[PDB]
Image (cartoon, coloured by chain):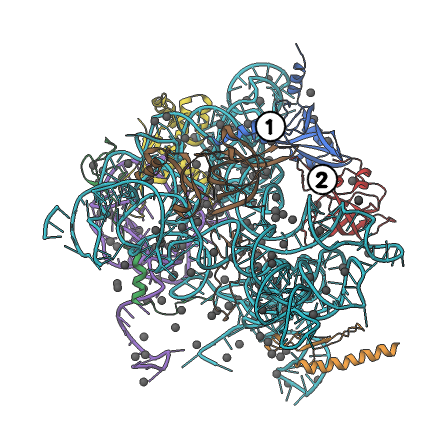
Chain colours: A red, B blue, C brown, D green, E yellow, F orange, G purple, H cyan
Amino acid sequence: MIQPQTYLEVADNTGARKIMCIRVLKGSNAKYATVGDVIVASVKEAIPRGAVKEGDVVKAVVVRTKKEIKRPDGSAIRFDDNAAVIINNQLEPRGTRVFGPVARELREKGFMKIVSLAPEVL
Amino acid sequence: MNRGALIKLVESRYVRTDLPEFRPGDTVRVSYKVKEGNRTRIQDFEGIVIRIRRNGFNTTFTVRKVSYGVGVERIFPLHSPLIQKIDIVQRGRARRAKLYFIRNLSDREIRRKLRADRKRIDQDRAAERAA
Amino acid sequence: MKGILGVKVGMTRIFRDDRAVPVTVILAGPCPVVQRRTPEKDGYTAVQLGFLPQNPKRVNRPLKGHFAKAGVEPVRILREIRDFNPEGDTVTVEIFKPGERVDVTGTSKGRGFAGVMKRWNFAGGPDSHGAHKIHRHPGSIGNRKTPGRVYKGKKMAGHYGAERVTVMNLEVVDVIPEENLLLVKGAVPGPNGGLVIVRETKKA
Amino acid sequence: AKHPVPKKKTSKARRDARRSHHALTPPTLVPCPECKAMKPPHTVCPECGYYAGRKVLEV
Amino acid sequence: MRHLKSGRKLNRHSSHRLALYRNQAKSLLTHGRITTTVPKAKELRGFVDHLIHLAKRGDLHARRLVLRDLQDVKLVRKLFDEIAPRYRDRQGGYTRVLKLAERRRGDGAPLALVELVE
Amino acid sequence: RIDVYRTSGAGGQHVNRTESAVRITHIPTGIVTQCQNDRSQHKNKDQAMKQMKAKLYEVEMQK
RNA sequence: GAAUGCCGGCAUGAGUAACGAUAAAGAGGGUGAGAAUCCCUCUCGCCGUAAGCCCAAGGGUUCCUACGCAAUGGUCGUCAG
RNA sequence: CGAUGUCGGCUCGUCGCAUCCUGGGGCUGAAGAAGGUCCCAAGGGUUGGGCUGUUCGCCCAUUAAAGCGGCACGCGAGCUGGGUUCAGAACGUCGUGAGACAGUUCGGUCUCUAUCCGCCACGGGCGCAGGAGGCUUGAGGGGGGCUCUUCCUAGUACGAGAGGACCGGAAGGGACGCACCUCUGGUUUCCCAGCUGUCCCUCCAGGGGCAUAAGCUGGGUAGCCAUGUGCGGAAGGGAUAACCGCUGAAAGCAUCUAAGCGGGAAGCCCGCCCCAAGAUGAGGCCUCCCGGCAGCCGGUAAGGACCCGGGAAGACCACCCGGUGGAUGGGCCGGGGGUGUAAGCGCCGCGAGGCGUUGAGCCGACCGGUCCCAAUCGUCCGAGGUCU
Ligand SMILES: [Mg+2]
Ligand SMILES: [Mg+2]
Ligand SMILES: [Mg+2]
Ligand SMILES: [Mg+2]
Ligand SMILES: [Mg+2]
Ligand SMILES: [Mg+2]
Ligand SMILES: [Mg+2]
Ligand SMILES: [Mg+2]
Ligand SMILES: [Mg+2]
Ligand SMILES: [Mg+2]
Ligand SMILES: [Mg+2]
Ligand SMILES: [Mg+2]
Ligand SMILES: [Mg+2]
Ligand SMILES: [Mg+2]
Ligand SMILES: [Mg+2]
Ligand SMILES: [Mg+2]
Ligand SMILES: [Mg+2]
Ligand SMILES: [Mg+2]
Ligand SMILES: [Mg+2]
Ligand SMILES: [Mg+2]
Ligand SMILES: [Mg+2]
Ligand SMILES: [Mg+2]
Ligand SMILES: [Mg+2]
Ligand SMILES: [Mg+2]
Ligand SMILES: [Mg+2]
Ligand SMILES: [Mg+2]
Ligand SMILES: [Mg+2]
Ligand SMILES: [Mg+2]
Ligand SMILES: [Mg+2]
Ligand SMILES: [Mg+2]
Ligand SMILES: [Mg+2]
Ligand SMILES: [Mg+2]
Ligand SMILES: [Mg+2]
Ligand SMILES: [Mg+2]
Ligand SMILES: [Mg+2]
Ligand SMILES: [Mg+2]
Ligand SMILES: [Mg+2]
Ligand SMILES: [Mg+2]
Ligand SMILES: [Mg+2]
Ligand SMILES: [Mg+2]
Ligand SMILES: [Mg+2]
Ligand SMILES: [Mg+2]
Ligand SMILES: [Mg+2]
Ligand SMILES: [Mg+2]
Ligand SMILES: [Mg+2]
Ligand SMILES: [Mg+2]
Ligand SMILES: [Mg+2]
Ligand SMILES: [Mg+2]
Ligand SMILES: [Mg+2]
Ligand SMILES: [Mg+2]
Ligand SMILES: [Mg+2]
Ligand SMILES: [Mg+2]
Ligand SMILES: [Mg+2]
Ligand SMILES: [Mg+2]
Ligand SMILES: [Mg+2]
Ligand SMILES: [Mg+2]
Ligand SMILES: [Mg+2]
Ligand SMILES: [Mg+2]
Ligand SMILES: [Mg+2]
Ligand SMILES: [Mg+2]
Ligand SMILES: [Mg+2]
Ligand SMILES: [Mg+2]
Ligand SMILES: [Mg+2]
Ligand SMILES: [Mg+2]
Ligand SMILES: [Mg+2]
Ligand SMILES: [Mg+2]
Ligand SMILES: [Mg+2]
Ligand SMILES: [Mg+2]
Ligand SMILES: [Mg+2]
Ligand SMILES: [Mg+2]
Ligand SMILES: [Mg+2]
Ligand SMILES: [Mg+2]
Ligand SMILES: [Mg+2]
Ligand SMILES: [Mg+2]
Ligand SMILES: [Mg+2]
Ligand SMILES: [Mg+2]
Ligand SMILES: [Mg+2]
Ligand SMILES: [Mg+2]
Ligand SMILES: [Mg+2]
Ligand SMILES: [Mg+2]
Ligand SMILES: [Mg+2]
Ligand SMILES: [Mg+2]
Ligand SMILES: [Mg+2]
Ligand SMILES: [Mg+2]
Ligand SMILES: [Mg+2]
Ligand SMILES: [Mg+2]
Ligand SMILES: [Mg+2]
Ligand SMILES: [Mg+2]
Ligand SMILES: [Mg+2]
Ligand SMILES: [Mg+2]
Ligand SMILES: [Mg+2]
Ligand SMILES: [Mg+2]
Ligand SMILES: [Mg+2]
Ligand SMILES: [Mg+2]
Ligand SMILES: [Mg+2]
Ligand SMILES: [Mg+2]
Ligand SMILES: [Mg+2]
Ligand SMILES: [Mg+2]
Ligand SMILES: [Mg+2]
Ligand SMILES: [Mg+2]
Ligand SMILES: [Mg+2]
Ligand SMILES: [Mg+2]
Ligand SMILES: [Mg+2]
Ligand SMILES: [Mg+2]
Ligand SMILES: [Mg+2]
Ligand SMILES: [Mg+2]
Ligand SMILES: [Mg+2]
Ligand SMILES: [Mg+2]
Ligand SMILES: [Mg+2]
Ligand SMILES: [Mg+2]
Ligand SMILES: [Mg+2]
Ligand SMILES: [Mg+2]
Ligand SMILES: [Mg+2]
Ligand SMILES: [Mg+2]
Ligand SMILES: [Mg+2]
Ligand SMILES: [Mg+2]
Ligand SMILES: [Mg+2]
Ligand SMILES: [Mg+2]
Ligand SMILES: [Mg+2]
Ligand SMILES: [Mg+2]
Ligand SMILES: [Mg+2]
Ligand SMILES: [Mg+2]
Ligand SMILES: [Mg+2]
Ligand SMILES: [Mg+2]
Ligand SMILES: [Mg+2]
Ligand SMILES: [Mg+2]
Ligand SMILES: [Mg+2]
Ligand SMILES: [Mg+2]
Ligand SMILES: [Mg+2]
Ligand SMILES: [Mg+2]
Ligand SMILES: [Mg+2]
Ligand SMILES: [Mg+2]
Ligand SMILES: [Mg+2]
Ligand SMILES: [Mg+2]
Ligand SMILES: [Mg+2]
Ligand SMILES: [Mg+2]
Ligand SMILES: [Mg+2]
Ligand SMILES: [Mg+2]
Ligand SMILES: [Mg+2]
Ligand SMILES: [Mg+2]
Ligand SMILES: [Mg+2]
Ligand SMILES: [Mg+2]
Ligand SMILES: [Mg+2]
Ligand SMILES: [Mg+2]
Ligand SMILES: [Mg+2]
Ligand SMILES: [Mg+2]
Ligand SMILES: [Mg+2]
Ligand SMILES: [Mg+2]
Ligand SMILES: [Mg+2]
Ligand SMILES: [Mg+2]
Ligand SMILES: [Mg+2]
Ligand SMILES: [Mg+2]
Ligand SMILES: [Mg+2]
Ligand SMILES: [Mg+2]
Ligand SMILES: [Mg+2]
Ligand SMILES: [Mg+2]
Ligand SMILES: [Mg+2]
Ligand SMILES: [Zn+2]
């Protein structure tokens, strides 16, 4: 459950540390982004000399949510933070690696690069 | 009519009897059927059970682990056909039913607050002696 | 246009192809046909069905004469299924097969005198910033001198629920004949113990 | 609010028509099988103190 | 909505309602029969029956449970020694409510008697 | 593209229900200009044409 | 017949709003024509730098007792300033 | 002018069409895709945010689109009171001055009770020529009406290429709506446990009150809920709009039209969902009832009402279930569920405590069982059927 104003950890090494969602890219008025959804966000904190800098307006895909995610098999999964991987206009990761686990929901939505780069797919 | 027994009847066909008993606080390994592309495989999820929500067949439980630096919680239906098996890897003794509080605890504090449950461990060793 | 009378017993989920599917269990049969409506007699086609067995001691003489004329023991509820004429004298869950789609009619839960927010999802008012005793009020109900009245059908507070609701195109997940149980995917109007009607769906 | 007020005196007709629902219903009474006094049903008879054909109350 | 909610409020907050029942229970168990409003009487039954049922059990624990509500040692002595034996073969239904014919003058309240069964 | 709206600030009732302020935005140039001095919308629109002539005379001068 | 006229009487709103701190009541016994409301007993709650006690100002018999309940008491009243 | 409250916001909308999107179409300087322009079309939809009191406007990120207007530039006996229109104070300016400014600046009391119409709900009465218990027909009315992306067709038609379809299929979303509580997640006022201070019971142990109208904390069933689950927009049939035609004169040719016929929209009429015979035009079907003097009196029939135990029904009323030939509520019993190993005793420790007995004890609503308690006993209404 990500929405505008929501801060996300960025789980890549593009250099961004925290971004703030400013739109969820799912039609004209989606209220919330969940795992596998794309957002537009502002970069609020970033480490020096990264590929991205503070103030940049980026796109990202949500790879972890603190609101639990429900699966058709009746199970669910939930993480300690809300996290995203910053992407380009082709839904490809702008970083070389991704940190921490990511949700398997990513696979079916066409984020294979990210899924393979992740240390664990849960 | 007995509406409850009717529901119990419908549920009876889907009930599991092969899974071991555990309590909130135990450390458990859950072998889960997982789908990747066109194949199925087994993926193990091991962590502390922090909650068992009882409603007969509709019982579910929650397992928490730290994964590559990130807290993760999975909620499993106790009778899901997707669970290959559950392995008891350790018995912990808690003094309450819901262990939400461990979410805010260091690893050291968790280990301190959740002491090894020596009674239920000894019991385990008493079984696994087959005649 | 097949249909049967039933009672809502409760909800569960079953597992089907590694999927949890939510269901309401319905005790539908068995229903004796206690009168048939014909075009020649009644101007239309239907079957009056009975459900559940009733204590004769509570059934007055007029009802009894109606029961007696048909070959049937006294029953708690009589209801017609329109444009249905079963060949048999009794309708059971056997009329539905897993995979068929059904419309289910029941009486929704009553909320009694309901507010404009609960009834109609109105926005109410702010809970601070000076808002004065109108946190859950409807706001304006009109204009001014033109038209100087309130429209018929204005959404306002009043009784809500305990009314006939039909949910359409529900999947029959299972039917269990030895128990007269119907499993329908998803949610059915009304309380457990509630009386419902199950019909072949009008959706294509 | 702005202190709503009656626009017109209510006529004798309309006032009285409003009271068309105000008449009392007489109390519902049954004879007490013991002492035959009238009393409300499902209460202990206050006249002899019997209920369900047995003595309950001192009179 | 009150759907399937059990228990009366009796226009009292949590602790007053509690103190009401205890006090009435004390009163009932002392005199064996009291008069109260119909709703107070109806609500009272279950509360006292439970206390009596513990007295039928007789053990130290039950005595301590009942003591939480009744508070008075002597009354509980009476509960266990004198009252409890009369119900040893009776399973529940230790109290009885019967409605009175005349209402209270000042507020029209319908009254009832509540009494321990023989 | 002449825009009209209500004046801002003091005036009383005859400033709350009156669109007395004007704004003349030139479409190709992108130059905007407003006025709100006098109570009349067209005594202001007179001014806004005047000032608008001035802004184009500035730009065509700057070329 | 009118002066938002003057005085008095009686209506409408209406058996409607309200009955004036959310500190809280319950039972048994007595008195009495009449008792949720008066007396007594037990239980429960509230105050306790007071919601207890003493003094001054002001009030002016409200103090005590006996006999009473038309009116005063926002209900009742056998009780009472 | 013996008062018609004045901007903006909020809430709730409704209407118009000179249509922003979606649907249909003509022309195109229309290859394709994408546009431009005009015609039909008001069914539905028409985002979040930065700035400013702002309407307006600019900007950010999107979108199928971010339409324009009416309704006292809708809506203050519905809310707000930031802006304007009081009394204070200050700046700039004007005036010798008191003071003044469509100049600015900080501050500044928005009134519990709805009589009538209107509207949302719910009843009481009488009517529907005999009286009753059920089940219905649907005149009429309301609700609903949105849309995107991806894949297949097919990298085919078109095209130098870059690009890239019509038609027809398939999958998945956004917002909205109805219902629901299995799952997820809330609340859960005393369901359980832990804790402090104090007073008390009874000294220890064990408990009780109070700290809120739960003292605090950790949890928490049912119920009520969304963030959670299911389902809906249709399909299809009919008549049309613009438009495209077939046949075809007046007018030897020609013309979609003058006689005829056809195709053709998210629109209209049906279809779906809900209300509905006060539809006084009061409908239909099934069953039950049969003495005194177009009236009146009494006692009854079919049946109903009262009274009582109650209910995911409910403000009262109504509705629904049950009333001893009964499981309706309370108790009790079993299960579920919550809490999480009670008291007591024993053992270890100087002690705080620990361990065992023990998943113990307590235990609201849920699913049932059990006549133990209470629905005792009863009472009153209620046909005798208008005429051709
Ligand atoms: Mg956060
Ligand atoms: Mg910076
Ligand atoms: Mg910077
Ligand atoms: Mg990390
Ligand atoms: Mg159930
Ligand atoms: Mg082990
Ligand atoms: Mg451990
Ligand atoms: Mg750990
Ligand atoms: Mg199956
Ligand atoms: Mg209700
Ligand atoms: Mg409301
Ligand atoms: Mg609603
Ligand atoms: Mg709502
Ligand atoms: Mg709703
Ligand atoms: Mg709305
Ligand atoms: Mg809002
Ligand atoms: Mg608001
Ligand atoms: Mg709100
Ligand atoms: Mg205010
Ligand atoms: Mg408030
Ligand atoms: Mg009008
Ligand atoms: Mg209703
Ligand atoms: Mg479907
Ligand atoms: Mg006010
Ligand atoms: Mg009002
Ligand atoms: Mg007047
Ligand atoms: Mg009046
Ligand atoms: Mg009269
Ligand atoms: Mg009169
Ligand atoms: Mg309600
Ligand atoms: Mg209710
Ligand atoms: Mg409430
Ligand atoms: Mg109940
Ligand atoms: Mg009650
Ligand atoms: Mg209350
Ligand atoms: Mg009250
Ligand atoms: Mg309290
Ligand atoms: Mg207790
Ligand atoms: Mg009574
Ligand atoms: Mg001025
Ligand atoms: Mg003006
Ligand atoms: Mg005069
Ligand atoms: Mg004159
Ligand atoms: Mg006069
Ligand atoms: Mg006078
Ligand atoms: Mg008067
Ligand atoms: Mg009056
Ligand atoms: Mg009244
Ligand atoms: Mg009134
Ligand atoms: Mg009132
Ligand atoms: Mg009242
Ligand atoms: Mg009051
Ligand atoms: Mg009142
Ligand atoms: Mg007072
Ligand atoms: Mg009061
Ligand atoms: Mg009180
Ligand atoms: Mg007495
Ligand atoms: Mg006496
Ligand atoms: Mg007394
Ligand atoms: Mg105190
Ligand atoms: Mg002190
Ligand atoms: Mg003095
Ligand atoms: Mg004086
Ligand atoms: Mg004196
Ligand atoms: Mg005296
Ligand atoms: Mg007096
Ligand atoms: Mg008197
Ligand atoms: Mg008086
Ligand atoms: Mg007074
Ligand atoms: Mg006296
Ligand atoms: Mg005195
Ligand atoms: Mg005026
Ligand atoms: Mg006037
Ligand atoms: Mg609205
Ligand atoms: Mg047009
Ligand atoms: Mg179009
Ligand atoms: Mg075109
Ligand atoms: Mg084209
Ligand atoms: Mg055109
Ligand atoms: Mg439209
Ligand atoms: Mg419209
Ligand atoms: Mg529109
Ligand atoms: Mg906007
Ligand atoms: Mg703003
Ligand atoms: Mg603005
Ligand atoms: Mg601002
Ligand atoms: Mg502006
Ligand atoms: Mg932008
Ligand atoms: Mg206005
Ligand atoms: Mg104007
Ligand atoms: Mg106008
Ligand atoms: Mg306004
Ligand atoms: Mg108004
Ligand atoms: Mg007005
Ligand atoms: Mg203010
Ligand atoms: Mg101001
Ligand atoms: Mg200001
Ligand atoms: Mg003044
Ligand atoms: Mg000067
Ligand atoms: Mg001077
Ligand atoms: Mg002046
Ligand atoms: Mg001024
Ligand atoms: Mg101030
Ligand atoms: Mg000011
Ligand atoms: Mg106001
Ligand atoms: Mg009225
Ligand atoms: Mg009127
Ligand atoms: Mg009626
Ligand atoms: Mg007549
Ligand atoms: Mg119709
Ligand atoms: Mg009509
Ligand atoms: Mg319609
Ligand atoms: Mg291909
Ligand atoms: Mg091919
Ligand atoms: Mg197509
Ligand atoms: Mg297509
Ligand atoms: Mg769809
Ligand atoms: Mg939704
Ligand atoms: Mg549940
Ligand atoms: Mg739940
Ligand atoms: Mg939950
Ligand atoms: Mg719950
Ligand atoms: Mg308790
Ligand atoms: Mg407590
Ligand atoms: Mg309890
Ligand atoms: Mg201390
Ligand atoms: Mg204590
Ligand atoms: Mg003592
Ligand atoms: Mg102690
Ligand atoms: Mg105390
Ligand atoms: Mg207190
Ligand atoms: Mg506090
Ligand atoms: Mg709590
Ligand atoms: Mg919770
Ligand atoms: Mg939701
Ligand atoms: Mg959908
Ligand atoms: Mg023609
Ligand atoms: Mg056609
Ligand atoms: Mg169509
Ligand atoms: Mg459509
Ligand atoms: Mg009907
Ligand atoms: Mg109907
Ligand atoms: Mg009729
Ligand atoms: Mg009829
Ligand atoms: Mg009731
Ligand atoms: Mg009945
Ligand atoms: Mg009876
Ligand atoms: Mg029996
Ligand atoms: Mg029972
Ligand atoms: Mg029972
Ligand atoms: Mg358990
Ligand atoms: Mg222990
Ligand atoms: Mg122990
Ligand atoms: Mg020792
Ligand atoms: Mg139990
Ligand atoms: Mg039996
Ligand atoms: Mg009787
Ligand atoms: Zn008697």
Residue type at mark 1 is Tyr
**Residue H267 image position (x, y, % from top left):** 58, 60
Q: Would you say H159 lies left or right of H25 here?
A: right
- Residue that badge 1 annotates: B14
Quadrant hosting residue H44: bottom right
Q: Assign a secondary structure to mark 1.
A: loop
Q: Is residue A113 above or below residue H372?
A: below
Q: Which circle marks residue C144 in the picture?
A: none
Do residues under tags 2 and 1 come within 8 Å of each other at their CB atoms? Answer: no
Identify which residue is drawn at 66% across, 78% down.
F20
Identify which residue is drawn at 77% across, 43% down.
A110
Q: Are marks 2 and 1 on the same chain?
A: no
Label 2, label 1: how far apart the Cα atoms are: 33 Å
Question: Ligand 64 quadrant?
Answer: bottom left
Q: Nearer the viewer, residue B25 or H296?
A: H296
- Residue that badge 2 annotates: A80
